Length: 305
Ligand SMILES: CC1=C(/C=C/C(C)=C/C=C/C(C)=C/C=C/C=C(C)/C=C/C=C(C)/C=C/C2=C(C)C(=O)CCC2(C)C)C(C)(C)CCC1
Ligand SMILES: N[C@@H](Cc1c[nH]c[nH+]1)C(=O)O
Ligand SMILES: [Cl-]
Image (cartoon, rainbow, N blue to C red; front, side):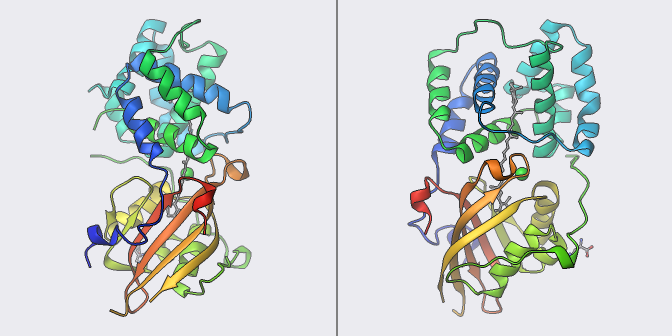
């Protein structure tokens, strides 16, 4: 067993690989087309999906960069936003690259508000997308909401130029007395239940003790994150205030055990308004420690167990 071979457990699991496909197509576009396409997607999605305000700490961390753009003339504002999309080497692009996903998302949330209000240079009136860009937007608009928000997040994360790391403060774990316990049809495995419950409580120090020293976590469409230091950093930087709603699973006992669970996850960016269809694929060692866990965004609800 290696981490890279563990990636192959439960090969029937059909991931929503239209998400990375669509990001690859998006990545080819002209920068002005990239910005305009996301503006159109975001405006249309906002007719039915309510996005949460960025956290106060996040907005403080992004404040100096946002102020710099706000002080620019309109041509320079457009150029700064194009620099980010083009992954140009500029001071702003390097600052942006140092930020956690949530800080990048909050930065663009604020620019979108300012563009709507007309205080930052908007997408030009009457703007027409390129041939390739129109088709990329059509693909996004045909996706389930959970896939759409994953495309937007990955587009945002990929901008800027790459190192110092800036992230939001780590919230205290949920008080013991108020914590929920999940139930999973077919799965009583204590490691899997404790995984779900500790993540739901933001209890990352308890969560990390479930792993082997060489264990890995593979987020959707990302390479495995290997070892307790890197996995705990990922938890603290990117995994706060999720709600995991596992539904059902299957347990296949080497003394190792493979377990697959399907259900839904909510991000604090959308709360109950977007339920992403998710699989968890666990490979546990004989002592019950996590050697490998993958989290997959599923192609459709038809992929739930
Ligand atoms: C750019 C841009 C603009 C603004 C864009 C904005 C503002 C977009 C905002 C998008 C947002 C806010 C998206 C949020 C997505 C969040 C997601 C998709 C979260 C998924 C999390 C998952 C699936 C976690 C699962 C996990 C589980 C379950 C585990 O068990 C272990 C941990 C982990 C793996 C993490 C404007 C309009 C100005 C136009 C110009 C360009
Ligand atoms: N950073 C943690 C590491 C840890 C080990 N187990 C749980 N957490 C600590 O200071 O203790
Ligand atoms: Cl999130």
